[PDB]
Length: 220
Picture 1 (cartoon, rainbow, N blue to C red):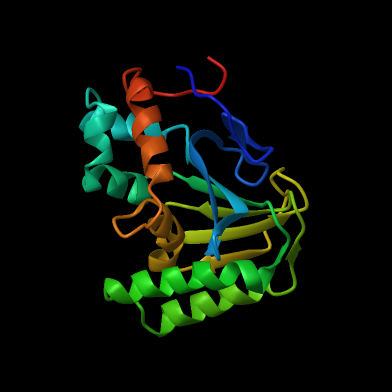
Picture 2 (picture 1 turned 180 degrees about the vertical axis):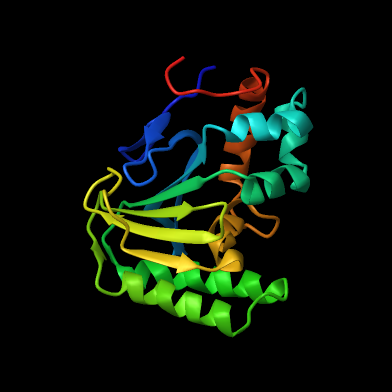
């Protein structure tokens, strides 16, 4: 029934959004902050948020209704269903400190290639996809408040969009047509080998109450 908005360093993630690209509607699964530990201070650089298409609740209901937040958090199978579920996911990275495209994209692409190799799915096609991934970021710069949108289609496509603020762009900058790569980004965020668990905790905390309703519709 009730999802709440999350604000990370004055960057707000509304509880619900609708894509001008797909016309689909998503609910906020979780949000957190990323950065680097440099010297004796942790410096925030980006805010990160994960949205799940509204139909995801009905999809996850069968296996995960009734389970507590504590149990979901310790269950890899649950996050695999989220990562690879038959619904669209939308990931928004908003900058707290200014970063060029190559600057921000470096660590993400490294984590992706690291995982793709890890699971034996990094051939020529996947390499080209990550090259195309890189190219899309190169002509971009992200002042504070600027955002990147990863649209993970369940049909094996990753759409990349860039925005000067937190609004969803009307058009996408690039389409990376590769199944393995399409889910790679989200895997590095909530997958088994994801370092920061803040988003997993957000998902574990927020989904059970929703799954109890068996379904989610925008504005009901």
